[PDB]
Image (cartoon, rainbow over all chains, first blue to last red; front, side, top):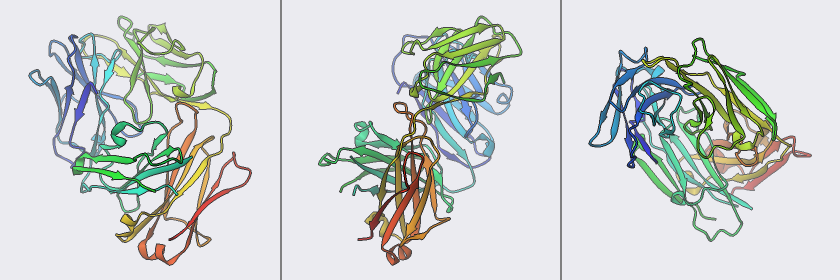
Length: 213
Length: 213
């Protein structure tokens, strides 16, 4: 990934949300970085930007509660959002303008994959990972009983097995906790190794579970 | 803030579709871009400066228009084009820039029956007092599908939840997971667990089952 985003995941109301967007590789481009957010099921909303001259622009709604900055020694761009409420729950993206424009949305040629932020009073909980064992064939992993929803990560064979993988959207169970399933279809020759790597960052839960017949 | 039209559309593979973007103010120096956002992924810059395709974007995509009215055309709609498309405009140099509301694009294809798999609760989960039985409907079209749970041929209700993937980039199909949740005692009280699938692609409902043990 070129623009690595980091954030706390689950935040309580009135706290200050602090997000980072780190440029992971060297680029001879004098680029600008823009922060955008997307509430669940909604459209893209501009937060602000910082140009190649470090000129920092803020959208009208953000100018009184957002601070955007850059640490060049780390190639790390920071966004701070004060006094968050549930209305600030969204996926937060950073994106690069290769022209160096800090207040432009028409040419964002490189995006971070987003960092989820859920603002709520409810306690963080790490998931349990269970194997969906085969009886082509199908296998998978059940990531159950966690909060908040994302950032959650599910890979197979540490990223080697990607074809035929269906990671389903998380559902909110009646217990108030989220559950998710990730399945993969493989030939009935299964001997070979099938491990699912799940990472719930808000709870520091890193589980590599082997699925066997 | 900019107006996109329509809010959503559907067409078949190989059809030509158009999305319109309109603004109140004229676009400054052709700063109008088109982004494609697939499910769970960051938006991707398809077109910048009204009509220039970014590298790697198939020539099936094209952009046109000027001033306040712009068009994104997909000349040969493909399954990998399932996404929400956003226009983004800049109107001055000081901070007047925004996104459109977005247009969802769905692709119609032939009826495809799902492949049904069933997964009993793992022994790890049975170590606790809960049991999750998973039913997987793989690669079906259209989305409409009925999933019914039977425990000793008794219909369940209120103890199952389902999740659906987005249209697949290769074959335009959906996949669905239905999780039935029971207590350990209730699970150990019964023998045959079945999930029955009703879909247009099946001449009759297809039931997959297992016997506990």
